[PDB]
Amino acid sequence: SNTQTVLPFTGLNTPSGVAVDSAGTVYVTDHGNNRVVKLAAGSNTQTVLPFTGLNTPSGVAVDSAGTVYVTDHGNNRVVKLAAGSNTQTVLPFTGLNTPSGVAVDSAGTVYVTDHGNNRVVKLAAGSNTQTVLPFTGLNTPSGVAVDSAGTVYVTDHGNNRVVKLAAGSNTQTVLPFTGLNTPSGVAVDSAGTVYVTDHGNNRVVKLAAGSNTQTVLPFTGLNTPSGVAVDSAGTVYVTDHGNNRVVKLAA
Ligand SMILES: [Cl-]
Ligand SMILES: [Cl-]
Ligand SMILES: [Cl-]
Ligand SMILES: [Cl-]
């Protein structure tokens, strides 16, 4: 599609992350209002998720159980809320510094871009022991995504590039995007196509698995886009950060 739609959220303030679940419900970190909002497909009435004490939250993810995970950026912590629960829990990460993105794989492993420490950390389901992933040379990494094969994709924000690590690998590779400015968000769909918010160029770009030629998606009028998600139908959702809105484009 080249007809973008603005989702009917209301009262957003410089939103920062977006996630979409298997039913098409959209979840947004409403960064400047210290809250997380949720909108079912076809609804025009958002709700606010009952997180507690968030400080300029940045990243959001939703797992197969519908549990919502948020990087509570200003509190140096990651929290999660089971669907229909009113009580969040704090995940047992250690040493985080303004965390910025979060992803969860099919095994429940939680991946976090530990932004201010230039690293990516992960926690397995039920574990208290985080691991630092063997990326190298990251500058203020800003988004993370993980595909069905366990390959981890990271927007290396300060180095204008996207890197990936295959499961079990100790050596990253750089994806062949071109011309990125301070990339923020990243998403990967079931076919392995990688979508990136090219933050400083006000555009969203994508790269099919095996391709060396990116495509620019036909969004218009974006301002410093900040997060991206893709649903099972291939619809791409972007937090249009500087325009206080969320926009989508069917494939
Ligand atoms: Cl901001
Ligand atoms: Cl901030
Ligand atoms: Cl930064
Ligand atoms: Cl910005």
Image: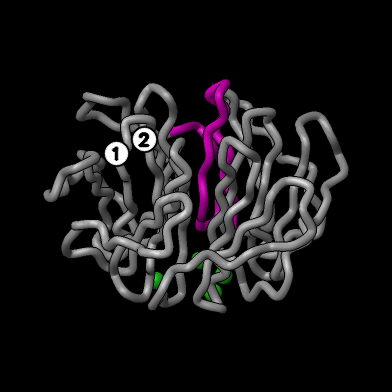
Does 114 lie within the magenta span? no
Q: Are marks 1 and 2 in contact (CB under 8 Å)?
A: no
Q: Which mark is residue 213?
A: none
Choose the circle earlier in sequence order: 1 or 2: 1
Segment tinted magenta in the rendering: 217-243
Q: Position of residue 147 (x, y in %)?
A: 37, 35
The amino acid type found where label 2 is placed reads Val
* Quadrant in which residue 34 is drawn: bottom right
In the rendering, at what x and y percent does residue 242 appear? 60, 60
Viewer-closest of 194 and 216: 194
Residues 63 and 207: in front is 63
Q: Secondary structure at mark 2?
A: strand
Read off the residue under disc 1: 151
Which of the pair 138/169 is nearer the observer?
Answer: 169
Instruction: Find disc 2 in the rendering and name its residue.
Output: 194
Spot the residue most to the right: 45
